[PDB]
Amino acid sequence: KVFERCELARTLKRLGMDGYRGISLANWMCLAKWESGYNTRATNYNAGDRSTDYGIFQINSRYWCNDGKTPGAVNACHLSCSALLQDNIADAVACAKRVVRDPQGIRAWVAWRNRCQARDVRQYVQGCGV
């Protein structure tokens, strides 16, 4: 599923993402926008290390989810990577929360550093009623 902007903002708010570990809803929006264009079925194979990024937040198989084909990987979110490809983003959100529980927080995603960090991200939630 490809979420519409405000649709996703309200869905994320309902899932308890606003201010989770100090991260504003607008930052989560900016992250999903740049990682996948708000697309839950998006996948990206990393030929360089044989890992794959899954879903709306493009979560990597090396440490977060299990896909069975990534060398010496772990599954911190305790989910099959398939769970990160559902239209229902509850599992993906649970996993994203797990990611930010680590020291890097939102910085875990390099795209966030490149296009969200230190920027005016208000535009992502304006008019959404969140």
Image (spheres, rainbow, N blue to C red):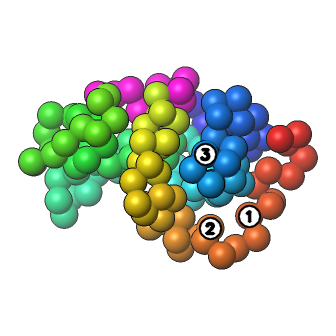
Q: Which residues are magenta?
A: 80-90
Tag count in the figure?
3
* Residue type at the position of mark 1: Val
43 over 108 or under it: above or below: above
Q: Which residue is mark 2?
A: 116
Picture coordinates of residue 68, whole percent (x, y) = 15, 34
Q: Residue at x 51, y 55 (%)?
A: 35
Taking the magenta stretch, the answer to whether it contains residue 35 is no
Q: Is residue 81 left or right of residue 91?
A: left
Q: Nearer the viewer, mark 1 or mark 3?
A: 3
* Residue type at the position of mark 3: Tyr
92 over 26 or under it: above or below: above
Residue 11 can be seen in this image? no
Q: Secondary structure at mark 3?
A: loop
Picture coordinates of residue 2, whole percent (x, y) = 61, 36
Q: Is residue 58 left or right of residue 2?
A: left
Taking the magenta stretch, the answer to whether it contains residue 88 is yes
Residue 61 can be seen in this image? yes
Q: Which residue is mark 3?
A: 20
> Does the residue at mark 1 contact the one at mark 3 (Cβ under 8 Å)?
no
Picture coordinates of residue 101, whole percent (x, y) = 44, 49
* Residue type at the position of mark 2: Cys
- First-in-chain label (1 vs 3): 3
Q: Residue at x 29, y 39 (%)?
A: 76
Q: Nearer the viewer, mark 2 or mark 3?
A: 3
